Length: 432
Length: 107
Image (cartoon, rainbow over all chains, first blue to last red; front, side):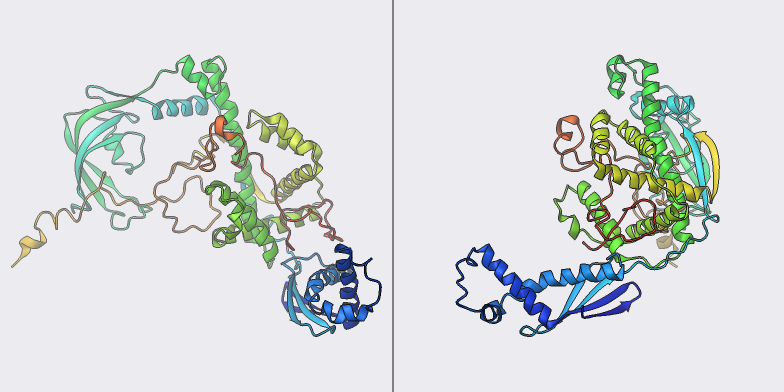
């Protein structure tokens, strides 16, 4: 093969293949009799016209047609003898083609560069052994009661989780600031449209008393025009209300996924539901800490090929929830996916190198556990277990993710992972 | 001698205009978002805690089991799409003990 294996820059290697003039004239000629076979005129051809005339005159048009295929034949030929896995996208830049002469084309694609594992032991991860304890079960169920609470009033008693109606006239550092007043605002104690100090001056009093409270805006408080200043607020209590606990009626409580509607069945139901959410979110917690530590610790020039792949999956994922844009996903703004995808590539490169270094292989029983528990999140596990385990293509996909998780925990066994046992209030319940 | 303009009401009115509950809305960018991304200026108008989108996908018609069927598009039971037939054909020696296909180029 007549080739010029150059390199544009780093990964972008330019195998400028020039198909030999003789080889083109023969390959086109061999394709032209195939055209005649497609139209069945090959057997009607009595050989009265020699093959040179039908190739040079008639087949003068049908040249680039054949070259489109020929470029790919020399491509797969080249990368096999070069031992390159074709990264990038094979870019056939056609120099030119004369009548039956040599066809120069610069095939620009990427190669895989040197990967360096480092700072593996330096990575500080946390392993929060979180469960939904009886405190979390009843506490969060109680929050659900107080979110779906029946509105009521009471005569002069406010607490931390009640409701109030006030009109205030505040001043920050002595200035009647932006607004100053806020007339007849209904403060459901348990909201987050005000800072501590303010809410603490509301949630321990009764209606009739019109007083002031002293609050101060934090140093962390991102509003600099308020930050550090002490705000005096003349709170006028006019209404004392309560967001009263509603009835956990059998016909209501059953609707949370309980058959008979037993309270103990709801506590059990939210145990398994909140834990199904929880342990998957613990997985995301520990994994993303390890993953960020990996990228930040490690250096490699990242192939645009794999970036395009991860972007593409994120484009499908976006379009899926962005009205369900039917394969319009490809056109979605790349810049939204660019950085996070490139990150997800560095993940795949380093974790793949951790699979190599720690010589790992996916465990079938581990893949099984992943399937049955991921599917236990639905009322349709059986068809999922069948969809994966009766399909080697998708089972191999789930071996990929299993082995990727083995690669994470392989880095965790090296990394500074602080393991602790704690309640549901830890993980997602960071409402601050 | 026009001090009565500078002090007119409070300053101008109080300062300028009002609000539902008058404070200057500062962010508190911690949340369940652990120290991993940059995002030094998130903005984000309040939001809802952390986890919200779950029982609805906000697309097609997928929420209640009535209209969840057929258009069952909510990322129910996930899978990787690396491009091509995983191995493709040419892997030669990626030097791994099982073909990891998170991502793959060429097409």
